[PDB]
Structure formats: C-alpha cells, structure tokens
Image (spheres, rainbow, N blue to C red):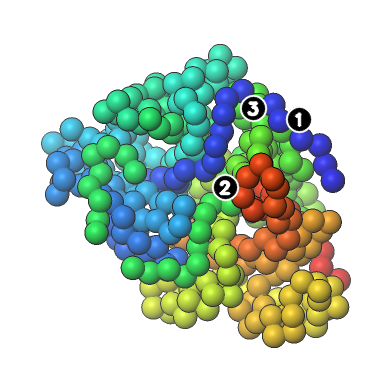
Amino acid sequence: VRKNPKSDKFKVKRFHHIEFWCGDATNVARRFSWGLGMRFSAKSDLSTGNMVHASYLLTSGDLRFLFTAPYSPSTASIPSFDHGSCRSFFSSHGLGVRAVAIEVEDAESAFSISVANGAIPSSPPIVLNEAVTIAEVKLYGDVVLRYVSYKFLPGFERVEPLDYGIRRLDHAVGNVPELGPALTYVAGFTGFHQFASGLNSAVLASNDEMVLLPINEPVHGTKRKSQIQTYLEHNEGAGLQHLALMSEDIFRTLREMRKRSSIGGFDFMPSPPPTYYQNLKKRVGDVLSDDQIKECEELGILVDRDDQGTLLQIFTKPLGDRPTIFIEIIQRVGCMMKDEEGKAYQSGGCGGFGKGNFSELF
Ligand SMILES: [Fe+2]
C-alpha cells in the first residue's frame, strides 16, 4: 500500500495515442502491423489531400499508433507538424516516439494550466473543425506530451484484420540524463504523484493511475556500463525508452509475435534459464497453473509479483537500428475490483513494473 494525493491540475482521462516520427511512415507502419497484430485504421497522406506529411494510424483495442513522415517541402491534418523539425528529429535521433498524447477534458485548459506551471510550450492549442482541440508541451528531450480533448482526428479518412491480444497502453517510459530535474519538471505542471541495476527511476501518475510515466536516470559507476547511459548516447539524448503494451493474454500474444520474428515481426530479449522457471512454480504458483508456468518458460516470459497482483512481462529488442526504443508486452493479473459506482475494472500499476525481476535470478 502506497500514498496517492490525487493532485492533478487538470482532468487526465486516459492515454490516447503515441506518434512516431519516421523517415518513411509507410514501411514502419507496415512492419509494425504484422509484428504486434494491429489494424490499419486511418490515414492522411497525399491520397487524402495531405501534401505535408504521411500519417498512418494502426490500432489494437484502445491502443493507437500513429506513424508520420514528411513529404518534400514543395493543408496538413496535424497542425503542430513542421518539416525541418520532423526531419531533424529523425536525422538526429532516428526512429522513435515524438508524441505521447493523453486524453483530457479541456486541452486548451490543460495546456493553459501546464504553461502557468513551468511547462515549456512547443505547440499552442488548436481546435480542429470545432471537434477536437490539440496542444503540446515539452516532456523530456524531443518528446512532447500532447494534450487531446474532444467535443481519430479530423482529416484522416477511415480505412474499412489482425489481433494478437494487445489492448491498450499501460505505461510509457523515457530515459533522461538526470532523473531529478525531469521528475520535478513533469510533476510540476501536470500535478502527478510518485507511484513509486545501473539506473534510477520513479513513476509519475495521473489521479486514477491509469497513466504511468516512468522516467529513468543513468548511474555512472563500477558495475557494467549503464544501459541507460547507452540510450542517451545513441539516441543522442533524453528520449522515450520503451512502451508497455497491455495484452489480455500474454500467451496469446507471444505465440503470435514470436512466430513472426524471423518473418518481419519483432525479436525478443534472451529469455531466462530453466532454473528461473523451476523457481517460478513455487513462487507464483496460486496465480499461474503448471501448464502456464510451462508456457512462460517456452515463450520466455518474466514473472514478478507483489501485494495486489501478479505481472507477466517480456521485452523486445530495439524496434529500429539504434539500441534505443524497444517494446514490452504485459499482463497484470490481480487487483480486479468491482464497485457499486461503476463496472468491474482493474487498478493501475497492478503488480507494479516487474521491479522484482533482475533480483529473482537468485
Ligand atoms: Fe516497463
């Protein structure tokens, strides 16, 4: 049990979409659709009227991935987009997340309050066809915290079939040179609270903790070379590290994804040895049955547990050429609570963040 001061400065409903700034929105969006089991939902390319950028939205349950690339400089759906910036971002950082957007009740207001509390402004509020309002502030590095509030986006034409299980964004993570400033800077204008080996982190969270922003900090010292000090060097600075994808069946998902590694999909971190799993049976027993412990071992899932739930997670190697951004698929078993005010659901951060992993290799 921990402390939650529910001190947001604005209403933060839930994670919306993640926007990648590529060099070619087309291939990445294709590669991904195959790899994570996501559907081609919408677009805003030349075929729609856009002559500034190509943008493809792939979805899976509430999870939405947006891929945008710039056209030749010689009418654009996303108003905050501008050539040179998209160019440079990609030229200097490579494939990666440019935007971490979250739903809010009033984007202009959210952006209003945020700016009055130290938030650095990149993009001003913009109402698009009296329907959606979009505003963007600086999170860390060249990643922006995009505010999206409603009455996908205007200008995108709907498209009309994969599904490996992915359902929503659990948490987004960003590595920075110094955890200190970053934390106070983010928590400062948002009003998030602290949810909770060559790295240091803390996790800010929205009121309902259905928005988790874990931030990492490198650790100079005699114990290998900080992986995070490695991300900062190849990514050329602070940038979004990994995205946790919430699946309702991590077994359904890893079967599907792993069957696709050698044919376009994603590769996975080397899995724990058989002694790791043998321990598992007598450590998470009551949560996962034998046939399930055996499935973890076969897909290479890492398990960790705490006072409210159990967590099954795994990790992907870099999504791109640089050992920078990678993906994670997870499942949080436990914490399910059915109240009389609403429907049955599950608290946020259930099981935590597998913190009890690297240790479990006793
Ligand atoms: Fe994570």
Which disc is residue 5 wearing?
Answer: 1
Relative to 4, say whether 334 is above or below: below
Q: CA distance from mark 3 to mark 1?
A: 9 Å
Disc 1 secondary structure class: loop
At which x and y percent is residue 2? Answer: 82, 42
Q: Amino acid at mark 2?
A: Ala
Mark 3 crowd level (few <14, some 14–19, many ≥20, 10 Å Cα)? some
| Residue for point 50% across, 59% down | 167
Foreground label between 1 and 2: 1
Task: Please indicate whether residue 288 sits to the left or right of residue 31 in the image.
Answer: right
At which x and y percent is residue 39? Answer: 35, 61
Q: Nearer the viewer, residue 138 or 108?
A: 108
| Residue for point 33% across, 25% down | 127
Q: Amino acid at mark 1?
A: Pro
User: Is residue 326 visible in the rendered structure shown here?
Assistant: no
Which disc is residue 361 wearing?
Answer: none
At which x and y percent is residue 164? Answer: 47, 70
Task: Please indicate whether residue 332 sits to the left or right of residue 12 in the image.
Answer: right
Q: Amino acid at mark 3?
A: Asp
Q: Is the residue at mark 3 in contact range of ligand 1, meaning its CB lies under 8 Å from it?
A: no
Mark 1 crowd level (few <14, some 14–19, many ≥20, 10 Å Cα)? few
Instruction: From the image, tell me which residue sits under label 3.
Output: 8
Instruction: From the image, tell me which residue sits under label 2.
Output: 172
Q: Are marks 3 and 1 in contact (CB under 8 Å)?
A: no
Foreground label between 2 and 3: 3
Mark 2 crowd level (few <14, some 14–19, many ≥20, 10 Å Cα)? many
